[PDB]
Image: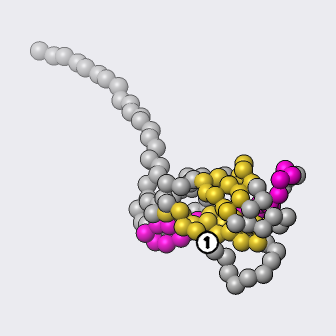
């Protein structure tokens, strides 16, 4: 009796690790997308967005409004819900500038904060640059 045989070898199969994999906890980042669509004298309304990298369930947010140039003791910051993308600021002095600091609240605390300035007036103005 007798017989023979033969074959060939080979292999290959690349892959990639899945993103969005937070092992540890940590406060969120700065809320980007701070634009002022509606801004009046003593009443403004800006809109922001959540941080692509929350790295933690948002419990709420904070919007600090104050006069960039004025006097006082502190700034009356307001806490928003974790499902708040926009906010309304009432009781602002016209013919001035206000700094809007947006922040989120997690199980760790308050992470980065997005600062956005907005003037109070009826005359629309926007240089757009930088």
Q: Is residue 3 above or below residue 50?
A: above
Q: Where is residue 25, by image quadrant?
A: bottom left
Q: Is residue 2 above or below residue 115?
A: above
**Residue located 36% across and 29% down the image:** 9
Farthest left residue? 1
| Residue 78: image location, x then y, percent | 58, 68
Mark 1 burial class by Cα count in 10 Å: few <14, some 14-19, many 20+: some
Quadrant where the N terminus is found in the figure: top left
| Residue 95: image location, x then y, percent | 85, 64
| Residue 33: image location, x then y, percent | 66, 52
Give the magenta range. 103-125
Name the foreground residue: 13 vs 107: 107
Farthest bottom residue? 73
Q: Where is residue 98, by image quadrant?
A: bottom right
| Side of 8 where 95 appears, left or right | right
Name the foreground residue: 61 vs 89: 89
Q: Where is residue 130, by image quadrant?
A: bottom right
Q: Is residue 123 above or below residue 66?
A: above
Figure colour scheme: secondary structure
> Is residue 128 in view?
no
**Residue located 43% across and 69% down the image:** 107
Q: Is residue 109 magenta?
A: yes
Q: Is residue 94 magenta?
A: no
> Is residue 16 in view?
yes
Name the foreground residue: 32 vs 42: 42
Residue at the spot of label 1: 77
Q: Label 1's element? A: strand
**Residue located 78% across and 59% down the image:** 41
């Amino acid at each position: 009796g007798s017989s023979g045989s033969s074959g060939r070898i080979g292999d290959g199969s690349p892959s990639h690790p899945p993103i969005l994999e937070r092992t540890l906890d940590d406060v969120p980042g700065p809320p980007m997308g701070i634009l002022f669509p509606e801004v009046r004298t003593t009443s403004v309304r800006l809109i922001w967005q959540p941080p692509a990298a929350p790295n933690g369930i948002i419990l709420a947010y904070q919007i600090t409004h104050r006069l960039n140039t004025t006097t006082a003791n502190t700034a009356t910051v307001e806490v928003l819900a974790p499902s708040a993308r926009q906010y309304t600021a009432t009781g602002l002095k016209p013919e001035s500038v206000y700094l809007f600091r947006i922040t989120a609240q997690t199980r760790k605390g308050w992470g980065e904060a997005a600062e956005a300035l907005v003037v109070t007036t009826e005359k629309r103005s926007g240089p757009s640059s930088g």
